[PDB]
Image (cartoon, rainbow, N blue to C red; front, side):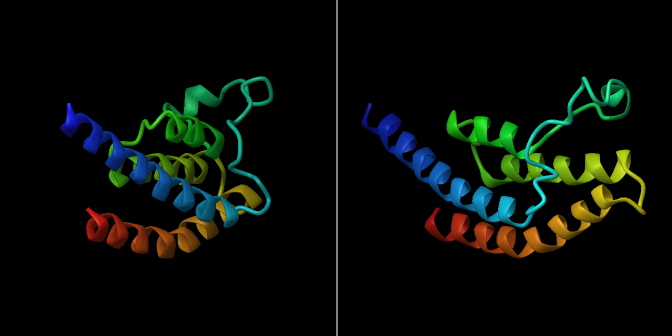
Length: 121
């Protein structure tokens, strides 16, 4: 139908916006601490601690499959990156600290994204 196509164009445009959001968030991780999944070869117990792992490459795969229906789902994944890190790693670690800075700096980007998503519909 014409409606299904209109819907698909909306999703494509959401994907376009979320791609720019993702690039902006990932720039706030210059050390690339959150770029890839935590390695289960190198941290063999990880899944005993963290039940829903997340990272920026995994978000990107979902994004490019148009697997985010709305900004809320996208933010859920971003929050997992931060919250998983802050649990697994202690406060006095470069990892924990990187997550805090990503959270703080990402807030600004996500604030305007929500306005853009509501505004453009």
